Image (cartoon, rainbow, N blue to C red):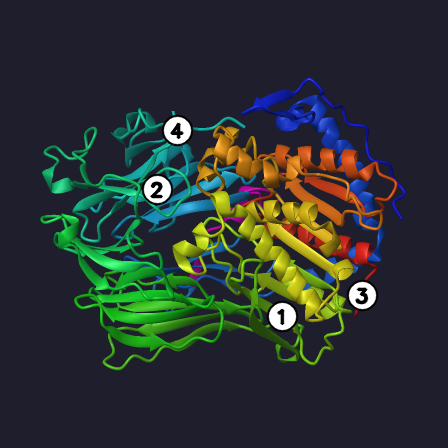
Amino acid sequence: MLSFQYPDVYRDETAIQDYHGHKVCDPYAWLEDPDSEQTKAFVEAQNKITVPFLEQCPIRGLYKERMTELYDYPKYSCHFKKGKRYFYFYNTGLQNQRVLYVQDSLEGEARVFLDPNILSDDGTVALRGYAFSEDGEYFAYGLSASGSDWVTIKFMKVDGAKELPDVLERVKFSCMAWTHDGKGMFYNAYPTSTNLHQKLYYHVLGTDQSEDILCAEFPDEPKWMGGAELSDDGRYVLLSIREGCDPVNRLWYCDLQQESNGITGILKWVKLIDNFEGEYDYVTNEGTVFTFKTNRHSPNYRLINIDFTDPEESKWKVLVPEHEKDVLEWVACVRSNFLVLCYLHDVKNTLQLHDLATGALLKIFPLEVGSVVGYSGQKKDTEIFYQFTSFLSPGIIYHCDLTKEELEPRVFREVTVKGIDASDYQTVQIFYPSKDGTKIPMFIVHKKGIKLDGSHPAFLYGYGGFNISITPNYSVSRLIFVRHMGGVLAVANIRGGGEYGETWHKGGILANKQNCFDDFQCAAEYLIKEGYTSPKRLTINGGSNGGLLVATCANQRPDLFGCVIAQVGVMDMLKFHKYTIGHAWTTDYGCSDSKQHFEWLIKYSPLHNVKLPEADDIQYPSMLLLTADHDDRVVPLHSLKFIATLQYIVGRSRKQNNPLLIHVDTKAGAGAGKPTAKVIEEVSDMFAFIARCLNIDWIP
């Protein structure tokens, strides 16, 4: 049972806004301020009920012990070469943050180069971006505290790992790009609030930030963000300008040879692509001929060559045409004249080597079914590394020496499932019909030989937005659910994602956002119909835009789910654009300032669709929201107002017996750069909640 009471929470019944003639009340609006005494008291009252609930069953401790043991495996990035040295990231297993190492050769002794763990007591200072100078002798790196999106950039001389005096503040959503003369580096800085007016600066090494040169600004377009990179030959600065989250950008360039006295003020920008109709992602150039990955006229992406000296679109060359189905995910240039292309084929990666001059296929790098999650090999490099992972594969790093006549990729590092036997499980891919008949991919992972009798707990994950493809990845936390809780794992590749290119994305955004929710509800119906699980035993989970997914699903089909866990969810679809970087998400969601968009948003906004189920035998699933009390990406008011609303409307009802809880982390932030210790706490909360709500016996 629930041996607690929900806290009394003040309702500001005067908080009424007219939206295009539709009056909307927001009685918990005051939870927008994370530092008020009122919001702090609300947070404290909620945690006072949630924490004892989660910690009461010995299950949480059993899970936490197993997680701590099974997550304690070596974690490596690919090696990458910079100048005359190799670097890689490595975590012995349970360090809060991974450490950057340096070695003089592949064969050589490695030494610690940058250890973020020494920057805090609790691993809450994290590396957030870095850039080596072109010659590899200098290193810039960003640090973020408590998951904040604000960054401080610091600098080191690589030889002897010497700290330099240079410090850059007010950095956020920033490029880091050194000019090839080694003189300095481009970065971005700013002059619940929304930051606007991001500018591009150039920092000369050995000077104060107050001396930095302003190189680009967009004072008539406060939402524009301009990121700089250097061409591979150092001649051009390429400025990619974004506004919102769609895969599109303007592309301007500056020929640095044409800057008379070097970088001294606003650069002589040539506005090569001066609209937001397509994405142009620089791959490499040979003189004035620039190869870009684009989605212009090509929703599954392709490679084009634009000659800056003859730049009309009718003159562009298609180097690697668009595939009819497979998405070109990313492209690198290596060993001067090779291209590495990574495709997504039915939600699994393939990796290929092509000739730069013709686009011809040269070599397929064989992979098992899963994802390529890391890669190294730049134009001047003569070898590649790439890292593969999958639901049952922690990671394999491959290496290939590209100077050889016959290429022979080899295993360079491999980590196997520790503790659990991977051969006892299997991963299947199925395609299920959505409401409108569209076939949606879903991966299912389960113990071999189970009976499809509906008896198994299931954990169904989704995201559904922003052109993000949800590809196979290794999660110890989910494998513990399978092995020790007898669960079935599922990941549904719903629309809004990038799995089938830009048409898949467009099929799940704006007026079509309800297609995401339909797809995800249909995934749940498939797992049930096919006998993997039953509604009372089904948990759904998502984070951020995926927290919106699962919150909406709880309101729309409370009868389909036993348990819902939403991490840092976007819950107030009418006000999201008003806070921090939320304005950028209007490219997926629309904005309530428009009547048309309001009419879409109101139908699904989780905060505005909490309703007691009409049927006497249906209640809301058990729900757990997780957020920290400060989060500059998804402001916590989303989850705070949502849980207040759930507890008032549904939790007060006699028929509601399933708990509706929030756990607010008040300890030095969660979010991106989350230390290992927090990850372990969070998954332990999640799976304890599931275990208690579904009364699942631990399987030792």
How much space separates mark 3 and mark 1, taking CA atoms?
A: 19 Å
Asked if residue 113 lies in the magenta stretch, the reply is yes
User: In this picture, is 106 found above or below 49?
Assistant: below
Q: At numbered mark 3, what does the secondary structure look like: helix, strand or loop?
A: loop
Residue numbers of the magenta segment: 110-124
Amino acid residing under circle 4: Tyr
Q: Residue at x 53, y 60 (%)?
A: 493
**Residue reaching furthest top?**
14
Q: Which residue is mark 2?
A: 175
The residue under label 1 is 445
Q: Amino acid at mark 2?
A: Cys
Q: Position of residue 310 (x, y in %)?
A: 10, 49
Of the pair 446 and 314, the residue shown nearer to us = 314
Instruction: Say which label, 2 or 4, has the lower sequence index.
Output: 2
Q: Secondary structure at mark 2?
A: loop
- Can the viewer see residue 412 in this picture? yes
Who's the residue at 46% across and 48% down the image?
A: 466
Label annotation for residue 570: none
Report if the CB atoms under discs 1 and 2 are less than 8 Å apart.
no
The kind of residue on which mark 3 rests is: Trp
Q: Is 130 left or right of 532, judged from the image as shown? A: left
Mark 1 or 2: the one toward you: 1
